[PDB]
Image 1 (spheres, rainbow, N blue to C red):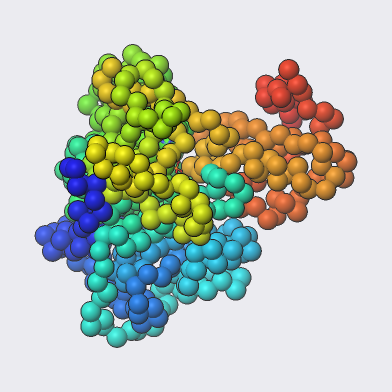
Image 2 (image 1 turned 120 degrees about the vertical axis):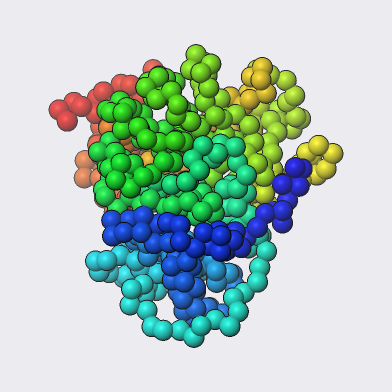
Length: 495
Ligand SMILES: Nc1ncnc2c1ncn2[C@@H]1O[C@H](COP(=O)(O)O)[C@@H](O)[C@H]1O
C-alpha cells in the first residue's frame, strides 16, 4: 500500500482511541505520580471537557492552546480538543507574552487551556484554568470529520526569521502510530512521555501508547537523567521510549545501564553517534533500537531503521526506509529519481504523513508542497532539504543539509537568519553565532563587533528563551582563515 499513502485510508485519532477504550476500558491509559487513569476514565473526562469546548466553539476547526507540564489533565485536554474537531497548540506561558500573542494571532488560537497547578500570569492572552471550568451541557453529538481534519499545530523556526505554523492531520498521527514494525517490540506499549508538546516527538510518545491500548507514563519526576529514567522504568513500568540523539548520548556516557528494562528505544533528531550506539547495544543486546528520521512537515517520522549488529561497523547508522503510510524518493539536481546506491540526492516524502501545510504562510505552502511523479502518478510531495544516499541494501544513509539550518535543543533554527538579525541591532557591525555542547545541551554563543555600549539586550528580551544565546560577547575582530575554532577558543579567554 499503495493507498496507505492516502490520508482517508487512516482512521481519525478519535475513532481509533474510541476503539481502544471500548476494547480495553480498564487497562491503564496514564501513569503519573498520583496513580493511574484507565481508558474509560480518560474518555469520560475528555468527553466532559469536550462538552465545554463545543459549548464555546460549536463548529469544528478551531485552534486551541494547551499550557502546562505533563499531567493527566494536559493529556485529557489533547483528547478533548481532538474530540471537538479542534486542533491543539502548545503555548509556553513562561515565554514573553508579546511572542505568544503573535503566535496566537498567526494561527488564530482562540483560547488557551491552562493546566498548571501554580498560577502563572496570562498577560492578556485568552487563558482558562483547566481545573476550574464551569459545567457544560452533555454534547448531543460531537462533530463529524475525516482523517484530513487538523489535529495540531507545531511552529517551526527552521526557515527565515518568522515562525511557520505546521498543521498536522489526524491521518498523520494514526499512520505514524498504527501497523508499524518499528513499534512491535513492547506488547504493553508503555511509553515514556517526556518530550514537550512543542515537539512532534510527543506525537509518538502520547499517541503511540493511547492508539495501541498502551500507557502514557508521564515524566512528572524531573528533567530526564539516568536516575529519573531508572525510576520511570523501575517504579512505573515504562518499556518504550524516545530519546533525542544528544540525550541518548549523554545517558549512555553517564550510566548506560539506565536504559535497562526498555524493550524499544527510538532515537534520532540528529545524526546518530555510532560510538554511543555501539556502547548502548553492546551493553543491551536484546534492546530494539530504532533510528527515526523525519521533518515536522511529514509528521514525526519519515524513515526508520531498526539497528542491527552489522550497522555497528558502519560510519553512520542508516535511517532506513519509509514508515508505513509514507513513501520516499531521492531526487537529483535535475529533479530525476536516483535509482542507484552511493549517489547523493534530496529526500522527498509522499503520503499520509504530509502536513496540510504552513497554516500561516500560503506562498510557502505552495512552494514547499508540490506534485511530483511517484510510480506512475503525480502525488503531493514535500521536499525536505535533507541530503542522503542509498546503500547497497536500498536503505537511506543521511548526509546533511546545504542550507544553514541547525538543530538546537529539539528545534530547527535558521541560524544565518537569526545572525543577520543580530547584525541589524544598532552599533553592531558584524556578528557570529556558534554552537557548543555542555552536558546534553547545545548552547548558542554570540560574538559581535561594534561600539562598546552596543550589547543586544533588547533583542534577547524579545526572543523565545530557546533562541537566546547563552553568552553575548563583544570581540575586537572576528578571526578569518570565518574561524569557528579560533572564535570558540577566544570565547574563553577568562570565562
Ligand atoms: N535520525 C536523524 N538523523 C539525522 N538527521 C535527522 C534525524 N532526524 C531528524 N533529523 C533532522 O531534523 C530535521 C527535522 O527536524 P524536526 O522537524 O524538528 O523534527 C530533519 O529534516 C533532519 O535535518
